Length: 92
Figure 1 (spheres, rainbow, N blue to C red):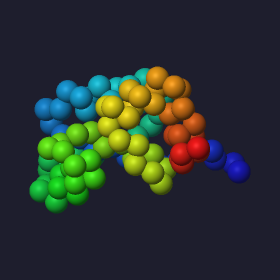
Figure 2 (cartoon, rainbow, N blue to C red):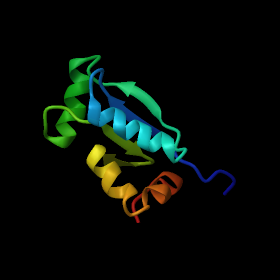
Figure 3 (tube, rainbow, N blue to C red):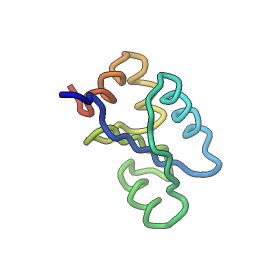
Figure 4 (cartoon, rainbow, N blue to C red):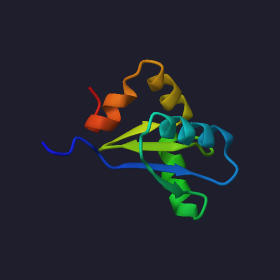
């Protein structure tokens, strides 16, 4: 259909190196995404960190699936599949 694009959202916090790198990496390819803070609140940071199971990491939501973080972004960009993930909004 006329409009091969999906809504992308990213959750990060002030003072996150691994997060910034991810955001820039996604912006480099030209992938637009909404930058939102998580540390802003306990719940926003809890639900996010609860998805990964660690202290705190960058969340990359593409389409209807949750990519991951700097690891998923770096691991995906290595294969060049992310381009299709942001275009289709789903996992092959």
